[PDB]
Image (cartoon, rainbow over all chains, first blue to last red; front, top):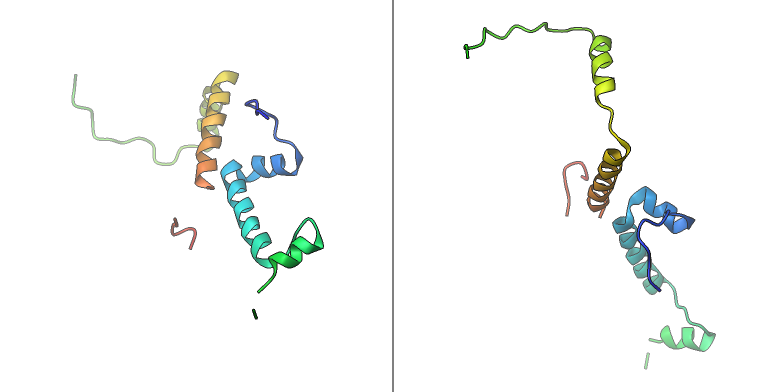
Length: 57
Length: 56
């Protein structure tokens, strides 16, 4: 997809961007990424979650 | 031109009279305000992207 400039900032993210600025939103998303990756064991299916959360210990 | 006299402006004039001149003169056309708004938004977006005393 290609994004046209000067788009009215709507949605939860657009409202976030009007408030904090786009750069801070990117930074907040990267922090959410560390949280999601470190504190959750997730997958599309349970087999994928379970394989990801494995430790012969 | 002449060396100016020793500086002696009134010390504490009335704010309202000053505001009566400064308020109309601060007016800016819509495209002037638009450029100001964009530049300033970009500067603040960068600010909100290190460390300073205020942060501590």
